[PDB]
C-alpha cells in the first residue's frame, strides 16, 4: 500500500492520513 504513496504522498496519503485522523 506504500507503493501508491510512492507517487502521491502529498495528496493521496495527505487526504487519507487526515481522513483517518485530524
Image (cartoon, helix red, strand yellow):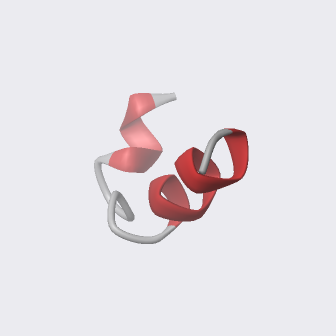
Q: To which quarter of the image does residue 21 belong?
A: top right
Q: Is residue 20 above or below residue 15?
A: above
Q: Residue at x 46, y 71 (%)?
A: 11
Furthest residue in direction right, as rendered: 19
Furthest residue in direction top, as rendered: 1
On the picture, is 7 further left or further right than 12?
left
Q: Position of residue 8 (x, y in %)?
A: 38, 64
On the picture, is 7 further left or further right than 19?
left
Q: Residue at x 69, y 40 (%)?
A: 20
Q: Position of residue 1 (x, y in %)?
A: 52, 28
Q: Is residue 12 above or below residue 4?
A: below
Q: Position of residue 2 (x, y in %)?
A: 40, 31
Q: Residue at x 45, y 47 (%)?
A: 4
In this rendering, the count of numbered labels is: 0
Of residues 13 and 8, the one nearer the viewer is 13
Q: Residue at x 70, y 52 (%)?
A: 19
Of residues 14 and 7, the one nearer the viewer is 14
Of residues 7 and 17, the one nearer the viewer is 17
Q: Is residue 15 above or below residue 5?
A: below
Furthest residue in direction front, as rendered: 22
Q: Position of residue 9 (x, y in %)?
A: 34, 57
Furthest residue in direction bottom, as rendered: 11
Amino acid at each position: 500500500d506504500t507503493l501508491l504513496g510512492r507517487m502521491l504522498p502529498q495528496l493521496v496519503c495527505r487526504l487519507v492520513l487526515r481522513c483517518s485522523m485530524d
